Amino acid sequence: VNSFSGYLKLTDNVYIKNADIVEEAKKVKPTVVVNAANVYLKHGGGVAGALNKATNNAMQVESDDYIATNGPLKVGGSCVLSGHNLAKHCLHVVGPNVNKGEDIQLLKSAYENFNQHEVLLAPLLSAGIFGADPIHSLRVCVDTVRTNVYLAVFDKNLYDKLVSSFL
Ligand SMILES: CN(CCCC(=O)O)C(=O)c1ncnc2[nH]ccc12
């Protein structure tokens, strides 16, 4: 039993809710919140900009030190950093950005990072400003992640389409 509430169960291990991941994170304090990161951990907009704003820019300060030490992530890769006031940990995961021409096949590799964590609060990778089809992203999530994932979908309209079209 865990503290996530109001989710629709899609599969044995995947759950979905119309929610703001920032507000969902501040209420659950999950062990892991997933950020929709880029390779530079520049949290300017989308999910990343919202998560970072909610940390009063502490996520960005920590991220800049990470990059100065380690260099950029790989597309499809991840790193574990602090969750600040939102979660114990933040798993920064880089899905491919279609608006940069990145290979959508890397979306599966991105979701594989979730399997290193027993339970996660997450957005749909490569959705939103990353330019992928959220229905495809949901399919890859369900077919790749084996750990328990609670997906927060900000837009009520897209949420309804994702549920209604789910196979
Ligand atoms: C709406 N999108 C896609 C567009 C932005 C992006 O591409 O990051 C989200 O990712 C998302 N999901 C869950 N809660 C969220 N709160 C703010 C954005 C957000």
Image (tube, rainbow, N blue to C red):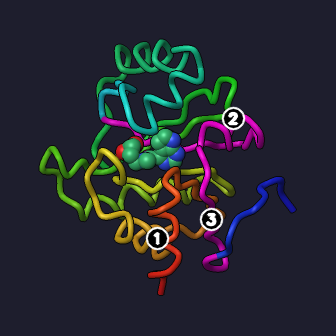
Residue at the spot of label 3: 147
* Left/right of residue 13 with respect to residue 135 in the rendered view: right
Q: Is residue 26 above or below residue 154?
A: above
Q: Residue 65 in the image: state x and y as whole percent.
A: 43, 13
Please name the residue shown 56% across and 51% down the image: 122
Which labelled disc corresponds to residue 87?
A: 2
* Left/right of residue 24 with respect to residue 54 in the rendered view: right
Question: Disc 1 on helix, strand or loop?
Answer: helix
Kind of residue at disc 1: Thr
Kind of residue at disc 3: Thr
Q: Residue 59 in the image: state x and y as whole percent.
A: 52, 21
Please name whichever residue, 68 or 9, is drawn nearer the observer in this view of the structure. 9
Residue at the spot of label 1: 144
| Crowd class of label 3 (few under 14; some 14 to 19; many from 20; radius 10 Å) | some
Kindly report the distance in space between the C-alpha atoms of the residues bearing marks 1 and 3.
Answer: 9 Å
Q: Is residue 85 above or below residue 2?
A: above
Please name whichever residue, 52 or 87, is drawn nearer the observer in this view of the structure. 52
Please name whichever residue, 75 or 138, is drawn nearer the observer in this view of the structure. 138
Q: Range of the magenta residues?
A: 10-38
